[PDB]
Image 1 (spheres, rainbow, N blue to C red):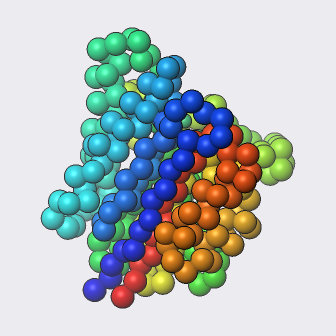
Image 2: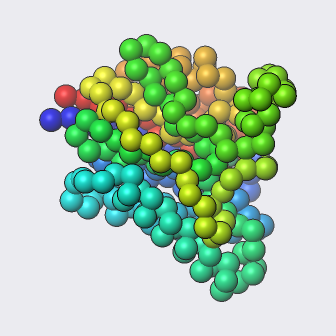
Image 3: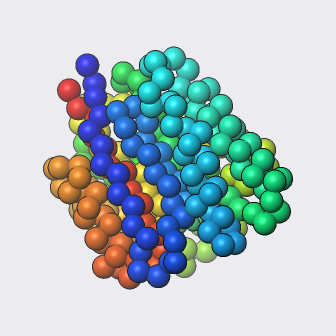
Length: 230
Ligand SMILES: [Mn+2]
Ligand SMILES: [Mn+2]
């Protein structure tokens, strides 16, 4: 009945030595993880988490999306702990994670960190995740302006943490964007909305990467654009 058309793109950017973002996109699961750590232990962290989510794409659909998602993330976060325990040569490594799991006309959203999920629906663009950062707290509390908001952040580091989990409606015509801060830091939401207007999902995704890079590509930039269609 309802199906996804998706496009994932990731680029190292114009500055960073390695790409510490990891991404997955398939017919049921979209997922993105921005890793961090000394010596690109951070590609390790982001891969471990994506690797623990992957099975949700091909597993028999669906059932309790949030619970599956919650379990997947906890599993990724235990892998990271195990990694750190086996080499304090990885101490402090971690990753953000934003993922969506689809089933029929519902979806589960799981999030922790400063990667983002957005919905384009009936011509409006909304951010369906909230950055888990000190700056976000400050702006929410009117303590700094949104502009001064242009680190200190929740992350999967192997220490137990519950991410945010939200069940939502998946509607024919929805367009979903997942992105790392390497997109949303250099590129405003008005410009992202423009790119999200491009019909073909691959070309929209390609445009976003191009726009981050035109913006100086200061960080790894990763996107998944996806449509819910009849
Ligand atoms: Mn990173
Ligand atoms: Mn980043």
